[PDB]
Image (cartoon, coloured by chain):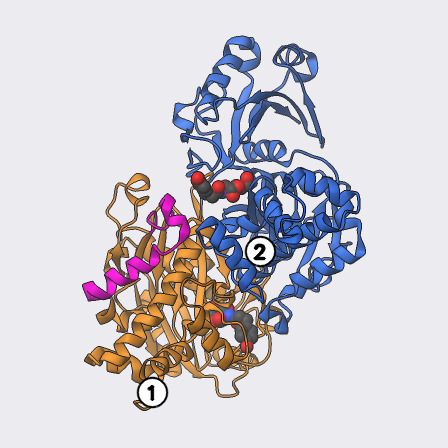
Chain colours: A blue, B orange
């Protein structure tokens, strides 16, 4: 798994080198603030990408970027493009129309994209966590799962389905991918046991109304701030973390950012730590409800957030509390939540870029 | 598109007429009370089946039924078995391990089934709604969708994905199947835009904790009765309807069973009617929340209950109220709930038997 990030110029020069004299997949991982776009080739995977700023905060700006690449890149390179797959930070329909976005305006339309980078019949727009799910599969496919994912706790069902150690393979069962970052992303890597095939199913779990436990007052406190029935993302996100911190300090310390709160928690600050426990309590509730609804074999937490918050999961008291909340469901009296193995990304890797490429394989 | 229930001996006879001198698919629709098993052949879908009482109330009695069938049947008939698929009223893993079940006792195990009816590599056990979802596909493939399904309302997304009228085909989009009957069943017919294929993913939406709207007291009341945080099935089931009717009458009238309540409502009783609106209010919350989480193109309400309570859905007032509640979600401010086309089964049909066959065709 190799990704190199280059200026657009160094990018152009890299693609003229012998190693890149080969069929290419155009890929793009588009976020609310930036996009990484470039080319990917083949059991190792090799991507070379350049970073763009989404300064105009508008999804149509990608069209301008694609043009730039086509004009600035030699035709010899562009003609090697066998497939073109990008991902965007919002719901996508028909792999062709993405929108509406929370942090960008406009609608991503595959039909308005240049066929030089998006060949007809071999092109797709993915949801970011749909690409991430494909990304998880690409890690598994390269026999390197244990290098990127660590077991948080092993579920009851793993040994029933798998002889190998937890975390060593994705496993022949449904894998629910959760990404608590800017937005709360989710996807279901469904497993069809009749053909032994994994299939990525995009979800919007973050946007469901939170069902209560013994926390009606806490939920109502947020309800009154937002003037909206809180959804999971409202508790599990940067603003969620900031909310949890305000609720812990109650005025006594002025507000700081989610980023600042995460830093303080890394330094042992009791208030920030408790905010972080709160944030994860709600993440574990997404997990327990989804564990029932989707009956997954595994749940995998992914993203730079998860990797960088390793200090939090490393702590056995934090981990035991998350485990307890994961089991906090009425259906656990039948063992449903206990079936599931939870894993977390433990090493940095842009799953989305790998996923766009992995998806391109299935179009080609 | 037809199914004749026959006696065991006159099943054996029926399977000698020349029209049934074809490869056969063994199928079985296992309910809590009765199981219908038999054989299927082909635009045209012809099935003939015999019924068994599940009077051991034990899922394992099936093997005796299987054994009997093979004993009381020609080797000219058994030799034409190409596939074998049955469905059961509980979760199933690996398409081969069914249960534990809320209704029956034991575990359905494909490995303990006779290969004469279940040719290895061409057989499966399905969850009941997993089969239902396959049945919905089969109806659509037989170009007879509009004969069995009526539109309750057309969603915003339909005319952009399909040029055919709503209700006339399943549609090239995800279809969430809900079966609000004795239990609450749910499955997602996922549409894969990469390869234009539908796949059926089993769900357990019924067992999710109910998120609130403005009904905290009503939920607390049931919570106190059940001594369990209510899930959608608690509000949307037989037990659910009985609860709604009781909260309506407040001991002013006698307590009535679900069937009693249903009948009374059809006759025009105001209290029973109020109970059924209450029930459908919670059914619509399953739909609005799943509309966000799973982003379906359609939602199809299936089952005998649904056909038999056609009177309820035909009332323009009840339907308007259902529609209103289907859009009662904070995400509707973005049009998410409005995207979805709702349909209901309007004519009797064992989708599950048809589903077992349709599944079989993917297995051969
Ligand atoms: O933003 C949403 C909900 C839909 C929505 C659309 C417009 C809007 O203004 C408000 C919400 N969903 C996205 C989701 O697609 C993505 O996978 C996730 C991780 O990046 O962040 C958000 O959860
Ligand atoms: O069985 C369950 C949930 C697990 C469960 C286990 C024990 C129990 O007492 C209660 C529920 N769910 C099943 C589901 O598989 C099925 O499709 C649906 C329609 O028949 O009925 C049930 O709701």
For this rendering, which residue is in front, B160 or A228?
A: A228
Q: Position of residue B129 (x, y in %)?
A: 44, 65
Q: As drawn, which residue projects farthest toward the front?
A: A252
Please give the chain letter of the residue carrying mark 2.
A
> Same chain for the residues at labels 1 and 2, yes or no?
no
Q: Name the residue carrying label 1.
A: B256
Viewer-nearest residue: A95 or A207: A207
Q: What stretch is highlighted in magenta?
A: B314-340
Q: Which residue lies furthest to the bottom in this view?
A: B254
Q: Can residue B325 be spotted in the picture?
A: yes
Instruction: Label 2: state its secondary structure.
Output: helix
Q: Main secondary structure of the magenta part?
A: helix
Q: Is residue A305 left or right of residue B137?
A: right
Ligand 1 under 8 Å from disc 2 Cβ:
no
Badge 1 marks a residue whose secondary structure is: loop
Q: Which mark is residue A286?
A: 2
Q: Which chain carries label 1?
A: B
The residue positioned 57% from the left and 32% from the top of the image is A356
Crowding near pointer 1: few (<14 within 10 Å), some, many (20+)?
some
Q: Does the magenta stretch include residue A211?
A: no
Left or right: B300 as drawn, with respect to A264: left
Q: In this view, does A246 lie above or below B55?
A: above
Residue in front for this viewpoint, B115 or A349: A349
Looking at the image, can residue B21 be seen? no
Q: In which quarter of the image is the N terminus of chain A?
A: top right
Residue at image position (59%, 31%) is A357
Measured in 3D between alpha carbons, the distance from the residue under mark 1 to the one under mark 2, in whole angstroms, is 37 Å
């Amino acid at each position: 798994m190799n990704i190199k990030e280059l200026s657009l110029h160094e990018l152009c020069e890299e693609l003229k080198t012998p190693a890149w004299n080969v069929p290419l997949t155009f890929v793009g991982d588009v976020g609310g603030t930036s996009a990484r776009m470039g080319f990917v080739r083949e059991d190792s995977v090799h991507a070379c990408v350049t970073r763009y700023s989404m300064k105009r905060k508008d999804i149509t700006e990608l069209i301008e970027f694609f043009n730039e690449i086509i004009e600035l890149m030699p035709a010899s390179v562009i003609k090697r493009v066998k497939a073109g797959v990008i991902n965007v930070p919002g719901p996508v329909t028909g792999g062709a129309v993405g929108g509406p976005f929370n942090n960008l305006k406009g609608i991503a339309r595959l039909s308005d994209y240049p066929k030089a980078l998006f060949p007809p019949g071999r092109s797709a727009i993915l949801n970011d966590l749909e690409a991430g799910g494909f990304g998880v599969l690409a890690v598994s496919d390269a026999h390197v799962f244990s290098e990127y994912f660590g077991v948080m706790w092993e579920g009851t069902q793993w040994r029933t389905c798998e002889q190998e150690p937890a975390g060593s393979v994705i496993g022949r069962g449904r894998c629910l991918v959760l990404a608590p970052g800017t937005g709360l992303g989710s996807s279901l890597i469904y497993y069809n046991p009749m053909n032994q095939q994994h299939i990525v199913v995009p979800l919007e779990l973050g946007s469901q109304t939170i069902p209560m436990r013994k926390d009606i007052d806490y939920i109502q406190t947020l309800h009154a701030e937002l003037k909206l029935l809180p959804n999971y993302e409202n508790m599990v996100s940067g603003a969620g973390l900031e909310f949890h911190y305000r609720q812990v300090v109650r005025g006594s310390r002025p507000p700081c950012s989610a980023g600042e709160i995460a830093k303080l928690a890394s330094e042992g600050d009791a208030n920030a730590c408790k905010a972080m426990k709160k944030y994860h309590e709600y993440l574990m509730r997404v997990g327990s409800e989804a564990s029932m609804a989707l009956l997954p074999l595994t749940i995998v937490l992914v993203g730079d957030n998860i990797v960088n918050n390793a200090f939090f999961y490393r702590n056995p008291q934090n981990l035991k509390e998350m485990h307890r909340e994961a089991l906090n469901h009425e259906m656990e009296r039948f063992g449903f939540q206990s079936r599931v193995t939870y894993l977390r990304q433990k090493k940095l890797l842009n799953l989305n870029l790998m996923g766009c490429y992995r998806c391109g394989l299935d179009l080609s």
